Image (tube, rainbow over all chains, first blue to last red; front, side, top):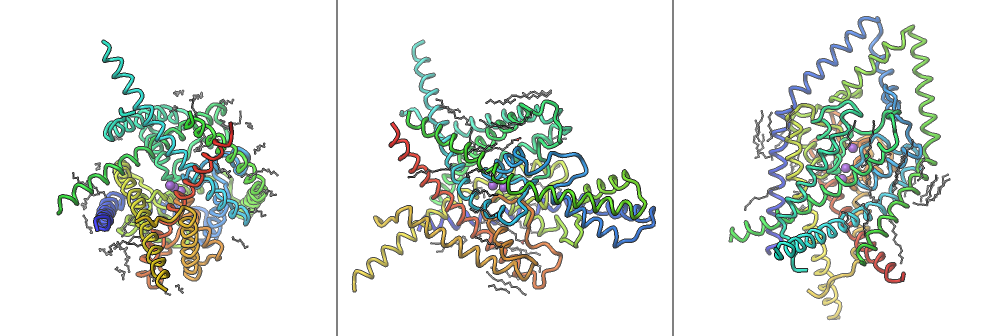
Length: 262
Length: 262
Ligand SMILES: CCCCC/C=C\C/C=C\CCCCCCCC(=O)O
Ligand SMILES: CCCCC/C=C\C/C=C\CCCCCCCC(=O)O
Ligand SMILES: CCCCCCCCCCCCCCCC
Ligand SMILES: CCCCCCCCCCCCCCCC
Ligand SMILES: CCCCCCCCCCCC
Ligand SMILES: CCCCCCCCCCCC
Ligand SMILES: CCCCCCCCCCCC
Ligand SMILES: CCCCCCCCCCCC
Ligand SMILES: CCCCCCCCCCCC
Ligand SMILES: CCCCCCCCCCCC
Ligand SMILES: CCCCCCCCCCCC
Ligand SMILES: CCCCCCCCCCCC
Ligand SMILES: CCCCCCCC
Ligand SMILES: CCCCCCCC
Ligand SMILES: CCCCCCCC
Ligand SMILES: CCCCCCCC
Ligand SMILES: CCCCCCCC
Ligand SMILES: CCCCCCCC
Ligand SMILES: CCCCCCCC
Ligand SMILES: CCCCCCCC
Ligand SMILES: CCCCCCCC
Ligand SMILES: CCCCCCCC
Ligand SMILES: CCCCCCCC
Ligand SMILES: CCCCCCCC
Ligand SMILES: CCCCCC
Ligand SMILES: CCCCCC
Ligand SMILES: CCCCCC
Ligand SMILES: CCCCCC
Ligand SMILES: [K+]
Ligand SMILES: [K+]
Ligand SMILES: [K+]
């Protein structure tokens, strides 16, 4: 009867959290959305007025452009899709459940293989993340034991959850700052935009509004892709570990509050 | 020393998997990509020649349209963003790490709150999924024990991993088929497109090329959103449980492989 109570309490808390978040976000974003819409309307009217065009023809032109931009065409020069490197970056995004959305399958037969490939790969990636977390905890315990032994001359040493959480937070902040050190001069962006992209990518959310390393020319274009791969991998591992630790702490807190409720 | 060997073997297998998948996907998609690009080029040339326009002006027009479409502006009459319900949809996609990408924050201040909200919510969602899996296993065990007891008259009854995997696969297939029964008449899609969307959404990949329930008018429009919410929640739970079970099986197989090798 305890487990059912815990499940119900968690569900209710999540629902309240969602309602509050929606209430805040609407008030934060509505006015900017409306201003952008009116700006686009005025620009469209000016363009349709200067060149004495019609209104339906521009609609057909824009529909064709939407189809083209879905295929992969963009106004600025971009790297081609579906080449060996582009396919490598697509499968890398697929197996980690990021899914930026800049490259998607378009033919029948290219979708079934996607289903089977993802089904077999996502489980392996999850197993890899779990093994990484176990190794990190073990090495932390060994380092702490060795440090204590060395300080004395002046297994059962596993650290608690709080210290693991602090270490993970510090590592994630350092990795994000180091990654945002680049991406600023290579691609024109603000530092805060780089941090926002790093958080969106590392948490495996992947909105797709900002995607890195596609400009059809990146000077060296060599070690840059390797660095991007390394940074994304490390960030994803650290963030997933942090989420698991936070979940453990939340479960302990729920246990306490339900014991208190009597 | 065994754990390090397991880690290294898993990493090597994942790398080989990625290379093979990239090769296959490129070989399947390159020609279609090239044909689409050529078609768009021909259409643009025809339009430019017909209306005696220049080439840079159309580029500026398309850049303005890209900026407008980065906001909540589409071609075929979509629902407004950030009113109250768009925010609810957005936060629902955020906390489940789907990230479709149809709605993104645009103002500074709306991004920091996103960071904190996601950091606190993703852990709770993961905990909810784990608790659901535990409850499902317990109820399966109870049902099996009760059925055996009833058949006889004509705790320690934990089912094995294989039966849990089979049950999860059957439930996921049934849920996906029932969901794809809808979305076919309400929105104009093929049945296979509905299945593809269901798999992409349930696995928390979320490419964003197909997003449901946005046309600014959906007849009843009251029960449709509730049904969409229920279906997505159930599918995500089932798929995550299946991924965890398959990961356990893969770990067992790796242990056997290491044991056999000397
Ligand atoms: C050697 C470690 C093996 C473990 C691999 C596991 C998971 C892969 C996860 C994430 C890879 C991120 C994809 C980015 C690819 C960019 C490549 C490019 O810019 O072209
Ligand atoms: C009562 C259940 C509590 C658990 C909730 C946990 C996680 C939420 C997960 C997924 C929600 C899917 C997106 C919702 C779509 C909005 C519907 C609409 O407006 O069209
Ligand atoms: C451990 C091996 C990982 C594989 C990393 C390969 C990524 C691709 C390398 C980048 C190749 C770009 C083409 C070179 C152009 C100079
Ligand atoms: C347990 C309650 C969770 C469901 C919360 C409400 C679902 C989303 C709102 C339903 C759609 C209302 C639109 C009304 C327009 C006719
Ligand atoms: C005894 C019944 C109490 C538990 C019911 C929980 C309802 C949550 C349903 C949504 C989970 C998919
Ligand atoms: C959905 C997330 C809600 C946050 C759960 C934490 C509960 C805080 C109580 C702490 C008491 C010690
Ligand atoms: C995410 C939890 C925060 C809850 C606070 C929401 C109440 C304020 C909403 C009204 C703003 C005008
Ligand atoms: C002028 C562009 C130089 C690009 C430098 C990137 C090299 C990073 C390699 C480090 C890998 C972790
Ligand atoms: C004995 C050395 C074990 C180190 C194994 C390397 C595994 C790849 C490192 C990248 C994972 C984040
Ligand atoms: C990385 C995905 C491939 C994992 C393959 C699993 C091992 C199969 C051999 C076990 C058969 C008994
Ligand atoms: C997922 C791994 C499947 C095996 C890949 C074989 C690669 C064949 C290349 C086909 C080129 C025509
Ligand atoms: C033409 C009217 C279509 C509306 C049907 C939606 C009913 C879904 C209810 C199912 C609840 C799980
Ligand atoms: C804390 C929950 C707030 C209730 C939602 C507000 C609806 C306008
Ligand atoms: C955490 C509550 C912040 C709400 C302020 C809304 C800004 C207008
Ligand atoms: C042309 C169809 C081939 C797709 C591969 C078959 C799925 C395993
Ligand atoms: C000019 C770019 C250099 C960025 C620093 C390298 C990453 C540590
Ligand atoms: C003007 C942008 C400042 C953002 C500061 C918040 C960083 C956590
Ligand atoms: C120019 C390609 C550099 C790639 C480095 C690979 C070393 C593991
Ligand atoms: C199984 C790995 C095959 C590697 C394919 C690379 C072809 C250029
Ligand atoms: C499973 C391998 C099939 C790849 C060859 C089909 C594409 C021509
Ligand atoms: C249009 C308002 C939606 C109903 C509010 C939900 C409160 C349970
Ligand atoms: C500009 C208002 C920012 C409010 C959110 C700050 C994060 C707690
Ligand atoms: C054109 C029909 C597609 C058949 C795919 C079968 C899905 C498993
Ligand atoms: C018209 C709204 C009906 C859906 C709400 C049902 C409450 C469980
Ligand atoms: C074009 C890149 C070749 C990759 C070999 C590892
Ligand atoms: C023992 C290997 C540790 C791996 C790198 C974090
Ligand atoms: C005991 C509750 C089971 C929940 C519904 C799958
Ligand atoms: C149960 C789905 C019925 C289909 C609605 C037309
Ligand atoms: K995602
Ligand atoms: K996306
Ligand atoms: K995800």
